[PDB]
Each structure stands twice: as C-alpha cells, then as structure tokens.
Amino acid sequence: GRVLSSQPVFVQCLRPVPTWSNNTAVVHFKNDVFCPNVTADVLRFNLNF
Amino acid sequence: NRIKCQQLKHELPDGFYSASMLVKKDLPKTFVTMPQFYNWMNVTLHVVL
Amino acid sequence: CTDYNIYGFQGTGIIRSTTSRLVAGLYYTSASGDLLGFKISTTGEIFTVVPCDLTAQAAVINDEIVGAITATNQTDLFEFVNHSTVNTYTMPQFYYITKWNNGTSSNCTSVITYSSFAICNTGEIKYVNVTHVEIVDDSVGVIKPVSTGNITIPKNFTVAVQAEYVQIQVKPVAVDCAKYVCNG
Amino acid sequence: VDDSVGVIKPVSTGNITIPKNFTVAVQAEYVQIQVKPVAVDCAKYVCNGNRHCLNLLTQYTSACQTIENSLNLGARLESLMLNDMITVSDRSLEFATVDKFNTTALGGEKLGGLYFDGLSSLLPPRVGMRSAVEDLLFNKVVTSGLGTVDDDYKKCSAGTDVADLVCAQYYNGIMVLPGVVDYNKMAMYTASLIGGMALGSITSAVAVPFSMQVQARLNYVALQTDVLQENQKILANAFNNAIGNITLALGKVSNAITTVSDGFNSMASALTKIQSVVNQQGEALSHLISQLQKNFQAISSSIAEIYNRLEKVEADAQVDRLITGRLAALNAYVAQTLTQYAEVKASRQLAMEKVNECVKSQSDRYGFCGNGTHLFSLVNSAPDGLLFFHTVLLPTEWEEVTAWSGICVNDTYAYLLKDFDHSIFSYNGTYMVTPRNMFQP
Amino acid sequence: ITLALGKVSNAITTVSDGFNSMASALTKIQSVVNQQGEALSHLISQLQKNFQAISSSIAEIYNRLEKVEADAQVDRLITGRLAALNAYVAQTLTQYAEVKASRQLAMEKVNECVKSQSDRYGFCGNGTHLFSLVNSAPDGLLFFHTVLLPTEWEEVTAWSGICVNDTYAYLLKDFDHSIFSYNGTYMVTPRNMFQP
Ligand SMILES: *[C@@H]1O[C@H](CO)[C@@H](O[C@@H]2O[C@H](CO)[C@@H](O[C@@H]3O[C@H](CO[C@H]4O[C@H](CO)[C@@H](O)[C@H](O[C@H]5O[C@H](CO)[C@@H](O)[C@H](O)[C@@H]5O)[C@@H]4O)[C@@H](O)[C@H](O[C@H]4O[C@H](CO)[C@@H](O)[C@H](O)[C@@H]4O[C@H]4O[C@H](CO)[C@@H](O)[C@H](O)[C@@H]4O)[C@@H]3O)[C@H](O)[C@H]2NC(C)=O)[C@H](O)[C@H]1NC(C)=O
Ligand SMILES: *[C@@H]1O[C@H](CO)[C@@H](O[C@@H]2O[C@H](CO)[C@@H](O[C@@H]3O[C@H](CO[C@H]4O[C@H](CO[C@H]5O[C@H](CO)[C@@H](O)[C@H](O)[C@@H]5O)[C@@H](O)[C@H](O)[C@@H]4O)[C@@H](O)[C@H](O[C@H]4O[C@H](CO)[C@@H](O)[C@H](O)[C@@H]4O[C@H]4O[C@H](CO)[C@@H](O)[C@H](O)[C@@H]4O)[C@@H]3O)[C@H](O)[C@H]2NC(C)=O)[C@H](O)[C@H]1NC(C)=O
Ligand SMILES: *[C@@H]1O[C@H](CO)[C@@H](O[C@@H]2O[C@H](CO)[C@@H](O[C@@H]3O[C@H](CO[C@H]4O[C@H](CO)[C@@H](O)[C@H](O)[C@@H]4O)[C@@H](O)[C@H](O[C@H]4O[C@H](CO)[C@@H](O)[C@H](O)[C@@H]4O)[C@@H]3O)[C@H](O)[C@H]2NC(C)=O)[C@H](O)[C@H]1NC(C)=O
Ligand SMILES: *[C@@H]1O[C@H](CO)[C@@H](O[C@@H]2O[C@H](CO)[C@@H](O[C@@H]3O[C@H](CO[C@H]4O[C@H](CO)[C@@H](O)[C@H](O)[C@@H]4O)[C@@H](O)[C@H](O)[C@@H]3O)[C@H](O)[C@H]2NC(C)=O)[C@H](O)[C@H]1NC(C)=O
Ligand SMILES: *[C@@H]1O[C@H](CO)[C@@H](O[C@@H]2O[C@H](CO)[C@@H](O[C@@H]3O[C@H](CO[C@H]4O[C@H](CO)[C@@H](O)[C@H](O)[C@@H]4O)[C@@H](O)[C@H](O)[C@@H]3O)[C@H](O)[C@H]2NC(C)=O)[C@H](O)[C@H]1NC(C)=O
Ligand SMILES: *[C@@H]1O[C@H](CO)[C@@H](O[C@@H]2O[C@H](CO)[C@@H](O[C@@H]3O[C@H](CO[C@H]4O[C@H](CO)[C@@H](O)[C@H](O)[C@@H]4O)[C@@H](O)[C@H](O)[C@@H]3O)[C@H](O)[C@H]2NC(C)=O)[C@H](O)[C@H]1NC(C)=O
Ligand SMILES: *[C@@H]1O[C@H](CO)[C@@H](O[C@@H]2O[C@H](CO)[C@@H](O[C@@H]3O[C@H](CO[C@H]4O[C@H](CO)[C@@H](O)[C@H](O)[C@@H]4O)[C@@H](O)[C@H](O)[C@@H]3O)[C@H](O)[C@H]2NC(C)=O)[C@H](O)[C@H]1NC(C)=O
Ligand SMILES: *[C@@H]1O[C@H](CO[C@@H]2O[C@@H](C)[C@@H](O)[C@@H](O)[C@@H]2O)[C@@H](O[C@@H]2O[C@H](CO)[C@@H](O[C@@H]3O[C@H](CO)[C@@H](O)[C@H](O)[C@@H]3O)[C@H](O)[C@H]2NC(C)=O)[C@H](O)[C@H]1NC(C)=O
Ligand SMILES: *[C@@H]1O[C@H](CO)[C@@H](O[C@@H]2O[C@H](CO)[C@@H](O[C@@H]3O[C@H](CO)[C@@H](O)[C@H](O)[C@@H]3O)[C@H](O)[C@H]2NC(C)=O)[C@H](O)[C@H]1NC(C)=O
Ligand SMILES: *[C@@H]1O[C@H](CO)[C@@H](O[C@@H]2O[C@H](CO)[C@@H](O[C@@H]3O[C@H](CO)[C@@H](O)[C@H](O)[C@@H]3O)[C@H](O)[C@H]2NC(C)=O)[C@H](O)[C@H]1NC(C)=O
Ligand SMILES: *[C@@H]1O[C@H](CO)[C@@H](O[C@@H]2O[C@H](CO)[C@@H](O)[C@H](O)[C@H]2NC(C)=O)[C@H](O)[C@H]1NC(C)=O
Ligand SMILES: *[C@@H]1O[C@H](CO)[C@@H](O[C@@H]2O[C@H](CO)[C@@H](O)[C@H](O)[C@H]2NC(C)=O)[C@H](O)[C@H]1NC(C)=O
Ligand SMILES: *[C@@H]1O[C@H](CO)[C@@H](O)[C@H](O)[C@H]1NC(C)=O
Ligand SMILES: *[C@@H]1O[C@H](CO)[C@@H](O)[C@H](O)[C@H]1NC(C)=O
C-alpha cells in the first residue's frame, strides 16, 4: 500500500565512504568537517552489513 | 505536491481541489485581558540534593 | 498573523480595528465557540478576529495549479521553492488569482466547469451563460399542433450519438456479526 | 374507477356509454430538481489550521480523502446534468410576456383568447421577471422565516464588522456554494417553455392563437368532426376558475367569495413540500457546526487550548479524541447528504420525463402527468425545482347507446371495422360510427 | 467518442459536445469503483478505537482484569463496535435502494429502446430515438443512443382539408397529415418529415 509519514529523507550532505580505504572515521552531528555549516538529525549509515 | 500528498496519487484528474498553506512558525504574541492593577508574585520550586 | 490570548480564548488570526459600536458585553463568539470580535474596556472601540489562512479552491489542469478561487487576495500558491507577474481579478462573489494577462490569449483547449464560471487552460475564466438553442424542441416525433399556416417541415436529417451510463449491481458483502464485535 | 376517455374501451356490441360533454381541471404538482451544493474542506474542519494537528491527520489521510471525494463527485454530476438540460431559446423567450398575449386583437384577442385571464397569472409582464404566481410563492419563503442568497465572500475576508452567520461558516472550512442554477435562469427556462406553445414557425414572427393550440390538442385524443363556439366557452371558464382557486390558496388574494374545492388538495401537497425543501440546507449545517463544542471526553472543545496546557508527548492523546470524534461528525453529515443527492437524482429523472412528454408533447400514458387524459401543461419556477400545471380532461355527460362491431350482409360477406376503437351504432334511424373515447359521430 | 476515452484515434483536434455526454459517464464510473474499497476500509479501521477503555483488543483486557470487572470494560467495546456496524449497514441499504431505482431504469431502457425503438420523446437520448447499442462497463451497462437531428426546413403554406363548392366537407383521417401545394401540385405529408 501507500502511506504518508514524516520520514528522514531530506539528504543534506552525502558522504560516500570507499570500501577499500579506511573504514573508520568520526561523524559529528553538529557542524562536522566533511560538511561545512549544517546540522542534521539522523545519520542513516547506509550499508550492506 | 501538497495536493498530491493529500490525494495519495502521483497524477491528479483535473478539477477543483481544496488547498491551503501551512501557516508560519514564529508569530508575535498578543494577550488582552480585563485591566487590573498589577500584583505579580514570584514563587519558585527549589530542589537541593 | 498573530497568536492571541483574549479573555481566555485562544488561537491564531489577524486582528483589525473597525468603526462600529455595539452596546453589549466584552466579546462576540460564533456558533462554534470561536472568537469573532471583542471590545476593549478602557475605550469604546471593538476589534475583529479573522483567521490567518482562509481556504482556497485551487484548480489544476495537467500537473499545474492554474488558479485559485480564493477569498482574500495575494494568497501565494505560486511563488517559490528556492530564492512573478501574478494577476488578481474580481468576480462578483470572489477574487481570482492567475498569472495570465487580460490581453490577447483567445485560445484555450480544455475547461474545468462550474455553475456560471468555467476555467480554461490559460487561466481565463469564461462566464458560463445558459446554452441558447433555436427552438426548445426537436421538431420530429413530437406533437405538431399547427395547421393551416406557414408551417416549417424538416427536410434533411443527421444522427448524433449520446452515451449514458446506468449502474445495475453492487458487489454484495456478507458480514458476520459475531466475529466482528469479538474475534472468537 | 376510470376517466372514460383515452383508456382502453374493451366493450363492444352492448349498451355502451360514450361521453358527450367535457370540462378541464387543473392539478398542480411540484418536482425538486436541484440542491445547493456544499464544498467542505476536510482538513480545516477537524482542526482550524493548527500546525500540530496536521501531523496527526497523516494517520487518517485515507478517511479524509473519501469525504472530499464523496461530496465533489456527487456535486459534479449535478452540474454536468443540469447544464445539459436547461436550454433557453431567445426567439420564444420574447413571446412569454403577457403584453404579447394581449396586443394581437386583430379579429379576436388572438395571442391570448378566452384563456387570457388564467394565463395572466402565469406569464411575466415584461421580458424577464417573475410572474404573479411565483410572486405569491416567494412571499412564502421569506415569510417562512428565511432568505439570503447573494453570499459574497469578499466581505468575509475584510474585518469591517463582526462576522455574519454566513462568514462564520466559511471560517470553519464550510463553503456554501452558489446554486448551480439561480433564480434568474429558472425564470428564463420556464418562460422559454411556455413560449414553445405560442411559437410554431421559426422564420416568421407571427404567432398562433392559443385557442388554436387547445383545439389542436383535442384532436390527438380523438379526431374532432364538428366544433362549436359553445365548447370553447365551457373549457375556458372552467380553466379560468381553476387558476383563481389556485391563486386564492397561495397568497390569500383573489376575487371570489368562498370556495372549498379539491384543487387545494393538489395545492396542499405542493406547499407542504416546498416548505420542507427550504428547511434542510440551513439545518444540516447548523447542526454540523454546533458539533465543534462537544469535547468528546477531553479537556476543552478548542485545540489550541489543549496544546497550551500539555506537552506534545501527552497532548496528542487528548487531541486524538477530538479528531476521531469530529471525523465521525463528518460521516454523519456526508451520509445524510448522499441520501439527498441520490433522492434528487430520481426526481430530476422524473422531471425530464414530465418536461419532454407532457410540457412539450401531450403524452398519452393515462394517469401520468395529472389525473386522466392529458391536454397540456404549463410550468413555473419554484424554490429549487419546477411547478407543473397539468390540465386534464373530465367528462360530465354520457350516451346510453346500443352498439355493434361490424356488418354481415345476407350471411355471405363479413365486414369488420379497421380501427378496433371505432364502433357502429344507429342514431335516430341513421347509422353512424364513432370512437369509444368521445362522442364524435 | 473513442478519442475522449483513451486518447487514441485518428483525427487532428475536435471540440464537440459528445465529450459532455461522455464526461457525465466517466465521472460516474470513476465514483462507482471508488465506494466498495472505502466503506470497508473505514469499517475495518474502527477496530483500533478503544471506546473509552484500556486497549483496542479484547484478549488484552481479559489478561489484566478479573471477570467481575473486565466485563464493564469490554462492554464499551461491544456497544461501541455495534454502533460501527449500524453506521456501515445504513450506508449500504442506502445504496441497495438507490441501485434498485437505477436497475429499474435499466429494464425500461433495455426493453423499450435497445429492443424496441421507443417513441416517448426525450427518453433514451435527446430527441427522436432511432436505435441504441450497449456495452459492458464496471457494474452496469453503457448505452449509445442514436437520435435524429434535423438540419433544414421547408417554409410551406398549409391547409387541413377540402370543402368543395361549399357543399361537401373533407377532413384528413390522420390528424398528423396536412395538405399543401408544391410547385402547383397538391401533396400531403406528415408534419414530422418532409415525405410528400
Ligand atoms: C439535444 O437536442 C437539441 C436539439 O437537437 C440539440 O440542440 C441543438 O444544439 C445545437 C448545438 O448546440 C444548436 O446549434 C447552434 O449552436 C450554436 C452555438 O455553438 C457554437 O457555434 C456558434 C456559431 O454557429 C458560435 O457563435 C458559438 O460561440 C459561442 O461563444 C461566443 C463568444 O465568443 C458567443 O458570443 C456565442 O453566442 C456562443 O455562445 C459556438 O462556437 C449557436 O450559436 C447556434 O445559434 C443559432 O441560434 C442563434 C440564436 O440567435 C442564431 O443567432 C444563430 O445564427 C443560429 O440560428 C440558426 O441559423 C443558422 C444560420 O446561419 C443555422 O446555421 C443554425 O443551425 C441555426 O439554426 C445554434 O444554437 C441547435 O440550434 C440546437 N437545436 C437544434 C434544433 O438543432 C442539442 O444539441 C441536443 N443536446 C442537448 C444537450 O440539448
Ligand atoms: C546489499 O545487498 C542488496 C541486495 O543484493 C543490494 O541491492 C541490489 O542492488 C542491485 C543493483 O545494484 C539491484 O539489481 C538490479 O537493479 C536493476 C536496475 O538497474 C538495472 O537497469 C540499469 C539500466 O536500465 C535501463 O535499461 C533497462 C532495461 O535494460 C530499463 O529497464 C531501465 O529503465 C533503463 O532504461 C542497468 O544499468 C543496471 O545494470 C540494471 O540492469 C533492476 O532493473 C534489476 O532487476 C529487475 O528485474 C528483475 C527481474 O529480472 C526484478 O526481479 C527486479 O525487481 C527488477 O525489477 C525492478 O526494476 C524494473 C525496471 O523496469 C521495474 O519495472 C520492476 O518493477 C522493479 O522495479 C535489479 O533490481 C538489486 O535488485 C538489489 N537487490 C537485490 C535483489 O539484489 C545492495 O546493492 C547491496 N549493497 C551494496 C553491496 O552496496
Ligand atoms: C373557484 O371555483 C368556483 C367554482 O367554479 C368559482 O365559482 C364560480 O364563480 C362563477 C363566477 O361568479 C359562477 O359563474 C356565474 O354563474 C352565474 C349564475 O349562477 C347562478 O345560476 C346558476 C345556474 O344558471 C346556478 O348553478 C348557481 O348556483 C347560481 O344560482 C351567472 O350569472 C354568471 O354568468 C354571467 O356573467 C358571465 C360574466 O361574468 C357572463 O359570461 C354570462 O353571460 C352571465 O351574464 C357566471 O358564469 C359560478 O356559478 C361559480 N361556481 C359555483 C360552483 O358556484 C369561483 O369563482 C372560483 N374562484 C375564483 C375564480 O377565484
Ligand atoms: C524570581 O525570584 C528569583 C529568586 O530571587 C530571582 O532570581 C534572582 O535574580 C536576580 C537578578 O538580578 C539575581 O541577582 C543577580 O545575581 C547574579 C549572581 O547570582 C549568583 O550570586 C548571587 C549573590 O547574591 C546569588 O544570590 C545567586 O543565587 C547566584 O549564586 C549577579 O551576577 C547579578 O548581578 C544579580 O545580582 C539573583 O541572584 C537571583 N536569585 C536566585 C536565588 O536565583 C528571579 O529573577 C525572579 N524572577 C522574576 C522576578 O521574574
Ligand atoms: C405565408 O406565406 C405566403 C407565401 O410566401 C406569404 O405570401 C407572401 O407574402 C409576402 C409578404 O411580404 C409577399 O411578398 C411581398 O410582395 C410584394 C409585391 O407583391 C405583388 O407584386 C408581385 C410582383 O412583384 C406579385 O407577384 C404579387 O402577386 C403582388 O401583386 C412586395 O411589395 C413586398 O415587398 C413583399 O416582397 C409575397 O408576394 C406573398 N406571396 C404570395 C404567393 O402570396 C404570406 O404572407 C405568409 N403569411 C404570413 C407570414 O402570415
Ligand atoms: C339495451 O338498450 C335497449 C334500448 O333501450 C334496450 O331495449 C329496451 O329494453 C327495455 C326493457 O325495460 C324496454 O322497456 C320496456 O318496454 C316495455 C313495453 O315495450 C313494448 O311496448 C312498447 C309500447 O308501450 C313498444 O314500443 C315495444 O316495442 C314493446 O312492444 C314495458 O312493458 C317495460 O316496462 C319497459 O318499459 C324498451 O322498450 C326496449 N327498447 C327497445 C328499442 O327495444 C335493451 O333491453 C338493453 N339491453 C340490456 C340492458 O341488456
Ligand atoms: C446571457 O444570457 C442572457 C439571457 O439571454 C442575456 O440577457 C439578454 O441580453 C440581451 C442582449 O441583447 C437582451 O437583448 C436585449 O434587447 C433589448 C430590446 O428590448 C427592448 O424593447 C423590448 C420591447 O421591444 C422591451 O421589452 C425590452 O425591455 C427593451 O426595452 C434591449 O433593450 C436590451 O438592453 C437587450 O439589448 C436580452 O433581452 C437579455 N435577456 C434577458 C432575458 O435578460 C445576457 O446578456 C447574456 N450574457 C452574456 C451573453 O454575456
Ligand atoms: C389588455 O389590453 C386591453 C386593451 O388593449 C389595449 O388597448 C388597445 C387599443 C391596444 O393599444 C393594446 O395594445 C392595449 O393593451 C386593456 O384594456 C384596457 O382596459 C381598461 C379596462 O379594463 C380600460 O381602462 C379604462 O379606460 C377608461 C377610459 O377609456 C376609464 O374610464 C377607466 O377608468 C379605465 O382606466 C383601458 O382604457 C384599456 N386600455 C386601452 C389601451 O384601451 C387591458 O388592460 C390589457 N390587460 C392587461 C394589460 O392585463
Ligand atoms: C584513516 O585514513 C585517513 C586517510 O584516508 C586518515 O585521515 C588522515 O590522516 C592524516 C594523518 O595520518 C592526515 O594528514 C594530515 O592532515 C593534517 C590536517 O591538518 C595536515 O595538517 C597534515 O599536514 C597532514 O596532511 C589527513 O589529513 C587525514 N585525512 C585524510 C587524508 O583523509 C585517518 O586518520 C585514518 N584513521 C585511522 C588511522 O584510524
Ligand atoms: C559556515 O558558515 C560560516 C558563516 O556563517 C562561515 O564563517 C565564515 O568564514 C568566512 C571565511 O573565513 C569568513 O569570511 C572571511 O571574512 C574576512 C573578513 O571579515 C576575510 O578577511 C576572510 O578572507 C574571509 O573572507 C566569514 O566572515 C565567516 N562568517 C562568519 C559569520 O563567521 C564558515 O566558514 C562556513 N564553514 C564552511 C566553509 O563550511
Ligand atoms: C487586495 O489586493 C490589492 C492588490 O494586492 C492590495 O492593494 C493595496 O494594498 C495596499 C497596501 O497598503 C493598500 O494600502 C491599498 O489600499 C490597497 N488597495 C486596494 C484597495 O486594493 C490590497 O491590499 C488587497 N486588499 C486590501 C484591502 O489590502
Ligand atoms: C352538452 O353538450 C351539448 C352540445 O354542445 C350542449 O347543448 C347546448 O347547450 C346550450 C346551452 O349552453 C344550448 O344553447 C344549445 O342549443 C345546446 N345545443 C344542443 C345541440 O342541444 C349542452 O349544454 C352540454 N351540456 C352541458 C351541461 O353543458
Ligand atoms: C492557441 O492557438 C494559437 C493560434 O490559433 C496557437 O499559436 C497556440 O499555440 C494555441 N495554444 C495552445 C496550443 O496551447
Ligand atoms: C415546377 O414544375 C414545372 C413543370 O413541372 C418545372 O418546369 C419547374 O421547374 C418546377 N419548379 C421548380 C422545380 O422549382
């Protein structure tokens, strides 16, 4: 079916982690270094775990 | 799009659709009462552990 | 558009000032318990509460909001997402807002109809008058109660197909009474 | 239990009874053809623009969707149907004036005739205004205790005065739309219909006298052989006295002494029905509006009061009973409305049959369009629908006459009448043949 | 008609009034499919409204309270849900009686017009009925009335019978017929068509 919802899909800033390089970083919610000024609510950490 | 999200359809038939706007967020307040001579108290709840 | 708190009543709207005097109590409610107006006590003037966002009746033709049968004026419905020539007309009973200039459109293909006002493709509202016919009759098969005069008898003919729909069945539903009020 | 003309006459070769003289009788009916449509905003009504409410209607956007589509797709079927039935011919509209029915005194008063006194109540004086009968009618809707139709909504969003009752309904998302056919088009539509009787020739502006119109409409029942001037009088005087007793029942003004007929009983069926029709539209809404003060087991009947006492994690439970309570209040209103849309759709279906078969055509279905054999029918406007005036035939005298149904000569040749409705009979030593409808030998 | 339906035909651009007959249908068929999936889904979704009780499921109630006091809580579920049926039932019997008028209408249109070329003016179309073809549709029929339409006329002086030498009268047997001269030749025709 279909449904309405308030979902987190407003992608401010996409940070593609490469598979090979270094699977370790930090992510700040408020004003990180990889994204200039902005502050988000969720980190959707998308993966094939 | 707000009409479409209220209609649950990606395409609308042409016609008349009751639409409005989300109003605002910040509004200046307004408080009117019967005029009275001011007698204002200041009671605080104080918890010390 | 403010947020009021007037004598215990509460809500949002637009407050104006008027020149009309009523010899009565403090405020004036509707039939639904909403504020319509109220009287300042220190003076005599009364004010009027109007809600901030009235409804509208926006008309869409093919994935585009053409115009809005609105009531106020400059309600937006056209403006922006990031970051025009938005006209405003005046019907007898409502305003009307569409970015088309009352110049030389003179062509629009599809209409959305209502009682005396149909809105065509380029925002142009036409006034729907009553359909004029030659004679309110289809002069064959009916009674022809005229003789011995200069009568008019039809010579040539053509056909015209007019389709109708008639609904003859509904899908029946058998409802168990006992299962529904308690699932076993 | 019959009106012995126009019906089947399944008796031959006996002492049959054939009617001689005739009179008319007018019986009025009412048919309601439209309802004033209402466009209801679903989202405004359950919460008057509150921001925290609309994040809780997302659970119930299925229920809110059907309520709008139940009302529009019932209303849109009206305007598509009504705009394809109401047609005004401007040629015949210029014959509906009562001055046209008086100005043709060449020879006789042609475009009126002996029926002029009754028709003076039905036709408008100038081209475009209501006639005498509707003026009596529309003095029984405002004096019924109601009446406003020119609802401007530009005045509603101004704040010049304290709000009108009508503008207060608009603030809660309830739009009383204008009538899909106003009073003026109904006045034009019915006046175009009566002009079809005075007009027969398109490309000649001369018009037929109305006495020729009735004399023609007698022939379709039975072929009139000999016509007399006395027959015109008794039809006309009974016609004009029928309209006066109609007019006296309406607004208590006519020129008579005291008369208790049964045309009141046709009229009392109408005046009860028209009285109810104006008394729905102002009452379903005012019941629906007044359900915005029933706090359905909650704190207060206004939503912005609730969000200024409680926090959002617990105020949602309180405002949930407002939502589900008010959403049921719409379905109580919607199902009452779709009752009326489907009920009118039967009556509007009935009005197309009565306009086409009887106002335009002198139908021969017995009993339909009045009571007895139909001669003609005149219409007038009314509050939301038409008001018919069926004119039926009525016999008064009869003829005890022995009959046969064919000749056998010298027991060799048989002869049968080609028409079965005809019958053969001797008449003061002379054998004649007549239909069994009228005594037209 | 075909161009209005599924936007495929072989033409250029035509704005007729057969759309206005067709738009009456396509609105109506669109509503008919949009009832049956919506009265039930409203009725089903009233099994989550705990009508002033603990929870919207019954077996939750009997696993918190004892039978002497759980009956009062489940009583509001019963009388609440029994009203939810009568809201559904009365909406249904509205439609059964409404269809019974339309199905009554369909027997008249099938018998008098599809099979018989009825002569009631205005019924089965608009004007004089020639024939009518039907097709299936979602829950009901779709008619195609074919009516007559005149285009030209004949300004003609008329009479309705002959009196010869002021002795004998003659009247036309059919009243619909009428007598008239036609380029110096007297003919007789019905007043329906020009068939002299
Ligand atoms: C049910 O049955 C009835 C009976 O069969 C059918 O009724 C017939 O319907 C047709 C079509 O509606 C009628 O034909 C004519 O319709 C014309 C309007 O359509 C347009 O074309 C005209 C030009 O001909 C345009 O002017 C119109 O444009 C409109 O918009 C402008 C604004 O820009 C306005 O100013 C206009 O007024 C229009 O609103 C449309 O594009 C209509 O104009 C035409 O008019 C006749 O009568 C008027 C009265 O004054 C005359 O002035 C005009 O000249 C026409 O008079 C006759 O003489 C000319 C000779 O030049 C003939 O060629 C015409 O045929 C006509 O006899 C006319 O009304 C038709 O009349 C009507 N009745 C019959 C017996 O056919 C219904 O269709 C059918 N369905 C329904 C639902 O009723
Ligand atoms: C963690 O694991 C998950 C699970 O494996 C990983 O997720 C998987 O990701 C896969 C892609 O990386 C996805 O695989 C397919 O995606 C296809 C879409 O892209 C295809 O098409 C483009 C180009 O298309 C153009 O041409 C085609 C025709 O040739 C047209 O149809 C297009 O419109 C364009 O014009 C190519 O460039 C790509 O290479 C792909 O070909 C799908 O199309 C595809 O399968 C579809 O068909 C199947 C039947 O054969 C059907 O079962 C399946 O559902 C697909 O059908 C979908 O799409 C069609 C398109 O018309 C639509 O009509 C159907 O309704 C339906 O939408 C594959 O889906 C995997 O599906 C996805 N999960 C699976 C099941 O493996 C994830 O990546 C991983 N995360 C990591 C490791 O990063
Ligand atoms: C509602 O309906 C009723 C029922 O018809 C109407 O009442 C009729 O009113 C008319 C007009 O007053 C009456 O007609 C007149 O009858 C007079 C004679 O009546 C007497 O004699 C007859 C027998 O001949 C008796 O049956 C009757 O009881 C009386 O004793 C005539 O003198 C009148 O004709 C004269 O004037 C006319 C012009 O007005 C000329 O045409 C004639 O040449 C003549 O000089 C006349 O026709 C009728 O009798 C009444 N009917 C009944 C049953 O009483 C109401 O008028 C009507 N209400 C309205 C219209 O508002
Ligand atoms: C309601 O009553 C409250 C209780 O008194 C009021 O709070 C008081 O607000 C005043 C504002 O001037 C404060 O005075 C300031 O104090 C700060 C430093 O605060 C600290 O040091 C003081 C020393 O006296 C100590 O009392 C405080 O508790 C803190 O440790 C100074 O820097 C300012 O210059 C100024 O002197 C009071 O200190 C404060 N009292 C408390 C107990 O919080 C409150 O304002 C009242 N609200 C109203 C009237 O609306
Ligand atoms: C019913 O239809 C009849 C047939 O059309 C109508 O008769 C026609 O009436 C018109 C009235 O405008 C006449 O036209 C007029 O003709 C005169 C001249 O007529 C005289 O001279 C001509 C030769 O030029 C001669 O043929 C005639 O016999 C007369 O001696 C003009 O001066 C006028 O401007 C106008 O054009 C027709 O002549 C006439 N035709 C016939 C055969 O009588 C009749 O009037 C219609 N009735 C109605 C509408 O009520
Ligand atoms: C159908 O209608 C026919 C025409 O009215 C009926 O025929 C009539 O039947 C009645 C029966 O009551 C007869 O009236 C009776 O007359 C006799 C005397 O008749 C004899 O004498 C007279 C002269 O005095 C003479 O004229 C006759 O020829 C007879 O020789 C009385 O004794 C009775 O009291 C009664 O008044 C009519 O005479 C008769 N008329 C004709 C022309 O035959 C017929 O009966 C009807 N059929 C039915 C109702 O089934
Ligand atoms: C929508 O349809 C309406 C109904 O058809 C239109 O109203 C009509 O507007 C026309 C414009 O031509 C009017 O025609 C009139 O002609 C008269 C002449 O009549 C005068 O003389 C007669 C007696 O001979 C007298 O009875 C009249 O009162 C006049 O004194 C002009 O005087 C008028 O001004 C006007 O030109 C129609 O009469 C009028 N119909 C009605 C019933 O009102 C309306 O205009 C249409 N709107 C559109 C098309 O936008
Ligand atoms: C129907 O028409 C008649 C007569 O027709 C009128 O006169 C013709 C000559 C034409 O010009 C027609 O176009 C015109 O309409 C109207 O009759 C009027 O009747 C009244 C009496 O009912 C007469 O009034 C009287 O006049 C005399 C003096 O002559 C006075 O003593 C009286 O006080 C009284 O006023 C009136 O003169 C007469 N009108 C004319 C024009 O002669 C009739 O009113 C009309 N019916 C309607 C409009 O309903
Ligand atoms: C995982 O790998 C990433 C690189 O892919 C490491 O981040 C990088 O760390 C190096 C130092 O080892 C940084 O280089 C230095 O950066 C500073 C920034 O001020 C600069 O001044 C120095 O001159 C030098 O360039 C590098 O910037 C940084 N970012 C990169 C290159 O992506 C990360 O530390 C590794 N995580 C581990 C080892 O846990
Ligand atoms: C995120 O946004 C903030 C602003 O809200 C950025 O801070 C801004 O940084 C720039 C660059 O340093 C400042 O401009 C500088 O101005 C001085 C003169 O005053 C000039 O000499 C420098 O060369 C430069 O042009 C700007 O003033 C400053 N704004 C504020 C209000 O702090 C911040 O850099 C952004 N971060 C990113 C890049 O994501
Ligand atoms: C209705 O629309 C018009 C066009 O937007 C607005 O026009 C003027 O707005 C200015 C704002 O100060 C006023 O001072 C003028 O008096 C307005 N003119 C009028 C009468 O339209 C107008 O604001 C809108 N409605 C109103 C009454 O403000
Ligand atoms: C029944 O019809 C006859 C024939 O039309 C009427 O008889 C005429 O009546 C008038 C009186 O109004 C007399 O002046 C005529 O001489 C009668 N003619 C004949 C041939 O008898 C009779 O009046 C009608 N009956 C009623 C009750 O009106
Ligand atoms: C309307 O017609 C004009 C000329 O007839 C044409 O140039 C214009 O493109 C048309 N509008 C459309 C097709 O939207
Ligand atoms: C009338 O008839 C004559 C002879 O039959 C013929 O010459 C003339 O053309 C006819 N008139 C017409 C057809 O208008």
Image (cartoon, coloured by chain):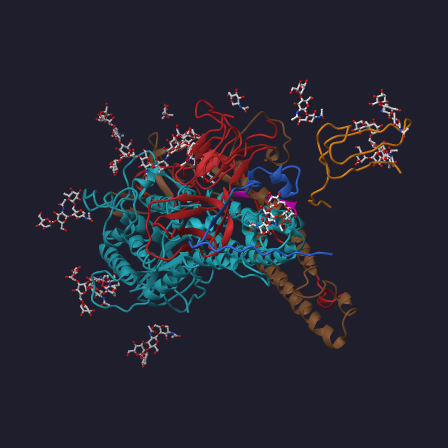
Chain colours: A orange, B blue, C red, D cyan, E brown
Q: Quadrant location of the C terminus of chain D?
A: bottom left
Q: Give the image quadrant in which the ligand numbered 7 is located.
A: top left
- The quadrant holding residue D273 is bottom left
Instruction: Residue E133: say if magenta.
Output: yes
- Is residue D258 visible in this depiction of the protein? yes
Q: Is residue D246 left or right of residue D1?
A: left
Majority secondary structure of magenta residues? strand
Q: Is residue D407 left or right of residue D106?
A: right
Q: Which residue ends up furthest to the right in the rendered image?
A: A20
How many numbered badges does the structure rendering display? Answer: 0
Instruction: Residue E144: say if magenta.
Output: no
Q: Position of residue C25 (x, y in %)?
A: 37, 57
Which one is nearer the viewer's eye here, D261 or D109?
D261
Is B38 located above or below residue D268 in the figure?
A: above
- The quadrant holding residue D3 is bottom left
- The stretch of residues the image draws in magenta is E130-138
- Is residue E150 visible in this depiction of the protein? no
Q: Position of residue B31 (x, y in %)?
A: 48, 49
Which one is nearer the viewer's eye here, D69 or E185?
D69
Q: Residue at the spot x=37%, y=51% of the render? A: C42
